[PDB]
Image (cartoon, coloured by chain):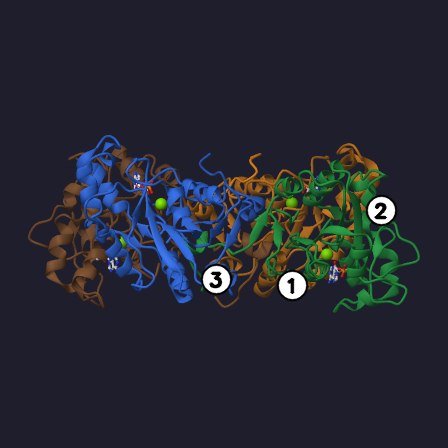
Chain colours: A green, B blue, C brown, D orange
C-alpha cells in the first residue's frame, strides 16, 4: 500500500451527479420575470471557517461546544467575517441574479445576536444594489424565530443555494429548486457533505 | 514546456454534464409498463472498430471509401463482428430492460446487405430472449429505407441510447429520452464526440 | 454499488494516486546524449490492442474458460492473421517514432506461444513504419508458470529499457536492473482485471491507454 | 469556453499531467535509516492557510491594490495575531508529525516582512504540537541588509529538505542542491494565480491542498 498505483478505469470513473454551470442556470431562467432567491451563508457565499476556527481555539479547543457559547456568536456576527473570504462561485451567481432584478435573501442558521454586521459585509463584498439587498435572516427553532422552511415560503423564494444537506431538504420540503454548492476541502466544518446525494443539481467548480 | 505541471483547480475541474447510472435510469422507470426502447450499435453496445480497421486497410488504405465498398459491408455484417467486443454498460442496460419486459430494438447506420448475422451476434452476446429481441434495423437516406427518426417514431421507442450526436438529436426530434453512451478512447471512429453537448443524460463509466 | 445517489465532494474530486507520471517528451529528454541502444516492448496492450483476437479465440475454443490460451490451434490463428484486427496504440507510435529517430534497435518480446510461422513481425513493422535497420523479428518467450520468461531475452539483447502494461513486464525489467516503463492497459481490453500501474514505483506514461 | 453545453469525452476525463506525485508515507520511507537532520517549511499556503489575514489586510489598507504588502501597519497586525485566523493544513500536520517522530529539527522560513515582535512561532508550535527540542523560531528571510535570503538560510542551517507551494521555494532548494518538495496551494487562497506544481520536475505531495 506504499505504491498503490492506479488504472484508467479508475482515472475516468465519474460519480453519477447532475452537474450544472452558472450559465446553464441563467439559461434555464430565460424569460422568467424577477423573483425571490435565497443563499445559505457559510461555505455557500463565504468561506467563514477562519472565524469558526478562532472561536473553537478560544472556547472549545477539543470540541464543538463553542457553537453554543453566546460569547462566540457576539464576536462572529460582529466583525470576524472581516476575515471571511467571499467565494467566486457566489460572486457569479449573485451578479447573475442582480442582472435579472431578482430579490436576494441570505438565510443563516447562526445564533441570532442583538446586533450583526454580516449584512453589511455581504453587501460590500458582493456590491449588491440597495434594490436587491435584504437584511440577513436568522432562522431557527426558537419561539420568536421562524424555521428555514417557513422563511423560504414566507418570502416566496423559488431557488435556494447551499452546501449542506439541510439546505437541500429545506428546498425540497417547500417544493422549490434547491441547488448545491461545494464546500471547500479546507473548511473546518467536517466531514464534507456528499454533493448530489438527493439527486439535486450541483454547481461545478463552486468550492472557491 | 517539458514540465507543464498542474494545480488543484485543474484537478477538481468538472464539465457541466448530467451524469446518470444504470441504477438511476432503472429507478426512474419504476411503475411504467413495458415499452419499446432502442440502441445504436457501433460504440454503443459493440466495440466494432476491429472490423472497420481491417476494412480500411483491405479496401481503402488511404481514404474512407471502404465505407462505400459493398464488399466491405458483406464482410462487416456477416462475420467480422465475431471480433467485436461487447460493452459492459450495454450488458447492464439490456439486462435491465429485459427484466422490465421491454421490447428492444437496434438501429444501425451500417449499409444494408442481403444477409446479416449481426442480429444473431447481439442476441447471443447479451442473452436477449426471443420475446424481447427484434431483427436489426438498417436506416439511411436510401428511398427504399426509412431514416433513423422515422424508425424511432414508427416503433414508438420511448428511450434511445447512442454514442453519437445524431443519436441524441434524433431522439430530441422525436420528443423522447435520448441517453448518451461514451465512445471508447481507442475507437477508430474519430474525433470523439462531446457527450453532453445537448444537455442530455450521460451514463457513467460507459466507455467499456 | 448499492447507493442510488452516492454524490461526491471536492476532496474526492481532486484526490490523486501517488504515481510517477511521465510523458514521451520527458522520456526523450532523459535520453539526450545517449548513444543508440537496444530497447524492448511487450506487445499485447502495450503496442497493440489485440483483445479482438483473444476474444474470438475464447469464444471459438473455450467459451467457459481460459483453456484456449494453451490450445495450439488458437495460437496458429492469432500469430498468422488475427492481428489484422488488432488496433495499434498511438502512445506506442510516439515511442517507436522517438526511438527510431534516436537510431535505437527495437525488440518485441511477447508471452504468446511460439508457432511454426508468424506474421506479427510484419504487422508491427508495417503499422508503425519501422525501418529494417531498427526492426528485429518478434521474440516469442512463451509463458511458463512460476517463472518469468522475458528476463532471459532482456539480458541477452542488452535492452536498457522495457515498455509494458503488465506487472511481469515491470518486474522483468527490475530483475535486470534496467528502466521499466509502464503503459496503461485500455479499459475495454478483455484481459482483466486491469493492473495497478505504478505499483512498483515505476514511471507510468500519461494517456497511454489508446 | 463560453459554450453552454461543452460536454466532455473519456480521453479528456482520463487525461493526466506528467507530474511526479508522492505521498507522505513514501517520503517517510525514503528517509528510513537516516539520522536526525534539519528540514524547512515555507509558511503561507504550505503549513497555514493564511489568506484570511491578507484579505482583511488588503480590505483595510489597499482596497484597490496590493500596496498593503508594503505597509508596516499591516505586517504589525499580520505577524502579531491575525494568524489566529489562519487555518493549519492537514498535509502539514502529517509531515511535521513524521519529522518529529524522526527527531529532526524543524525550521519555518517566510518571505513576510520582519517586525520587532511576532507571535507566529508560538502559533505554529501550539497548532502542530512541536516539542521544544524540535522547534525553532520563525526565520524572516529577505533583501534588507539586516537579514539573509531564503537560499542563505537553507545553507546556513544545513536543511536537507524544504517544503513549499511557490516556484521560488522549489528553485531555492535546487540552488542549494537539496530536495525540494511541492505543496499544493488551495483553490480558495487569495494569492493568485495558482502556480504550476511540478513545473520543475519536483515531487508533489498528493492531496496537500488542505
Ligand atoms: N466545526 C465547524 N467549523 C466551521 N463552521 C461550522 C462548524 N460547525 C458548524 N459550522 C457552521 O456554522 C453554521 C451554523 O448555522 P448553519 O446551520 O446555517 O450552518 C453552520 C455551518 O456553516
Ligand atoms: N473510421 C471508422 N472506424 C470505426 N467505425 C467507423 C468508422 N467510420 C465509420 N464508422 C462506424 O460505421 C457506422 C455506420 O453507421 P452509423 O452512422 O450508425 O455509425 C458509423 C460508425 O459507428
Ligand atoms: N483473457 C485475455 N484477454 C486478452 N488477452 C489476454 C487474455 N489472457 C491473456 N492475454 C494476453 O495473452 C498474452 C500472452 O503473452 P503475454 O504474457 O506477453 O501477455 C498476455 C496477454 O496480453
Ligand atoms: N494576495 C495575497 N493573498 C494571500 N497571500 C498573499 C498575497 N500576496 C502575497 N501573499 C503572501 O505573502 C507572503 C510574503 O512572503 P512569501 O514570499 O514567503 O509568500 C507570500 C504569500 O504567501
Ligand atoms: Mg452552509
Ligand atoms: Mg454508434
Ligand atoms: Mg501486455
Ligand atoms: Mg507559501
Q: Badge 1 is on which residue?
A: A191
Q: D97 or C130, which is in the foreground? A: C130
Residue at image point 25% right, 36% down: B67
Distance from disc 2 to disc 3, alpha carbons, whole Å, reads 43 Å
Task: Please say whether residue C19 is visible from this viewpoint.
Answer: no
What is the chain identity of the residue bearing mark 2? A
Q: Is residue A195 visible?
A: yes
At which x and y percent is residue D14? 44, 48
Q: Quadrant of ligand 4?
A: top right
Residue at position x 26%, y 61% in the image: B124
As helix, strand or loop, the secondary structure at mark 1 comes to loop
Q: Residues within 10 Å of mark 3 (few under 14, many from 20)?
A: few
Horizontal side of B118 relative to A107 (left or right) equals left
3 vs 1, front mark: 3
- CA–CA distance between discs 1 and 2? 31 Å
Residue count near mark 2 (Cα–Cα under 10 Å), binned few <14, some 14–19, many ≥20 = some
Residue located at (58% from left, 60% from top): D99
* Of labels 1 and 2, the one closer to you: 2
Q: Nearer the viewer, mark 2 or mark 3?
A: 3
- Residue C146 is left or right of residue A51, and the answer is left
The span from disc 3 to disc 1 (Cα, nearest Å) is: 30 Å
Task: Tell me: B152 left or right of B19.
Answer: left
**Tag 1, which chain?**
A
Most extreme residue toward the right, as rendered? A114
Residues marked 3 and 1 touching at CB (< 8 Å): no
Residue tagged 3: B26
Tell me where residue D57 sits by quadrant: top right
The residue indicated by pointer 2 is A134
- Quarter of the rendering containing residue C73: bottom left
Amino acid at each position: 500500500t506504499l505504491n498503490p498505483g492506479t488504472n484508467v478505469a479508475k482515472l475516468a470513473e465519474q460519480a453519477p451527479v447532475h452537474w450544472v454551470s452558472v450559465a446553464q442556470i441563467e439559461n434555464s431562467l430565460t424569460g422568467r420575470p424577477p423573483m425571490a432567491v435565497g443563499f445559505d451563508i457559510d461555505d455557500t457565499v463565504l468561506f467563514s471557517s477562519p472565524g469558526f476556527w478562532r472561536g473553537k481555539k478560544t472556547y472549545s479547543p477539543d470540541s464543538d461546544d463553542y457553537l453554543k457559547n453566546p460569547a462566540f456568536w457576539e464576536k462572529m456576527n460582529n466583525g470576524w467575517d472581516e476575515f471571511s473570504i467571499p467565494k467566486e462561485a457566489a460572486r457569479q451567481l449573485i451578479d447573475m441574479h442582480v442582472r435579472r432584478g431578482d430579490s436576494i435573501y441570505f438565510v443563516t442558521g447562526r445564533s441570532q445576536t442583538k446586533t450583526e454586521t454580516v449584512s453589511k459585509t455581504l453587501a460590500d463584498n458582493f456590491h449588491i444594489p440597495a434594490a436587491n439587498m435584504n437584511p440577513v435572516i436568522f432562522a431557527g427553532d426558537k419561539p420568536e424565530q421562524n424555521t428555514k422552511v417557513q422563511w423560504l415560503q414566507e418570502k416566496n423564494m423559488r431557488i435556494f443555494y447551499g452546501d449542506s444537506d439541510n439546505d437541500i431538504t429545506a428546498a425540497r420540503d417547500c417544493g422549490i429548486r434547491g441547488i448545491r454548492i461545494l464546500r471547500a476541502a479546507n473548511s473546518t466544518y467536517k466531514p464534507l457533505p456528499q454533493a448530489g446525494a438527493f439527486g439535486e443539481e450541483v454547481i461545478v467548480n463552486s468550492e472557491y
